[PDB]
Image (cartoon, rainbow over all chains, first blue to last red; front, side, top):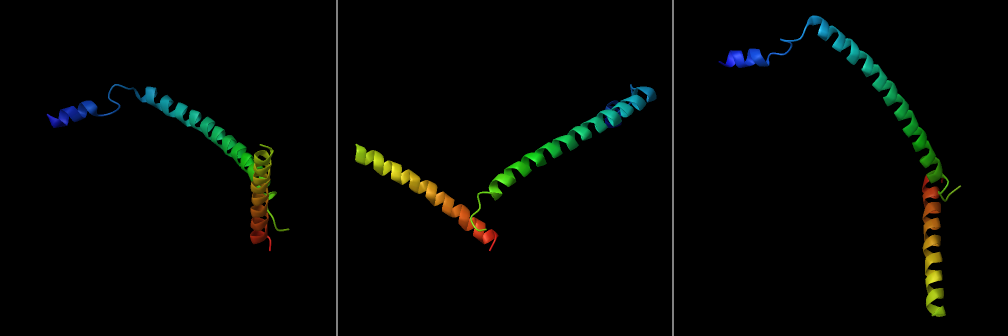
Length: 63
Length: 32
């Protein structure tokens, strides 16, 4: 019984090799896109940080 | 009333001063 319920849960059964080969391709792409988005964000945040830091530096007493 | 107001006003300016101090003290620990 177990071995079947597992064979049913076994992944990929229904799907084709092509229906997969593209799904991977896509994920590869949509993945680059998301990293460029990540990069950009990171930069923008660090710029924001630089801004805050500058401010804080100018509130210091001692030369 | 005027005495209240004035007392307040001075107290506030005090807090502002008190903060500027700290900034300078930080500046010291950081520079000197």
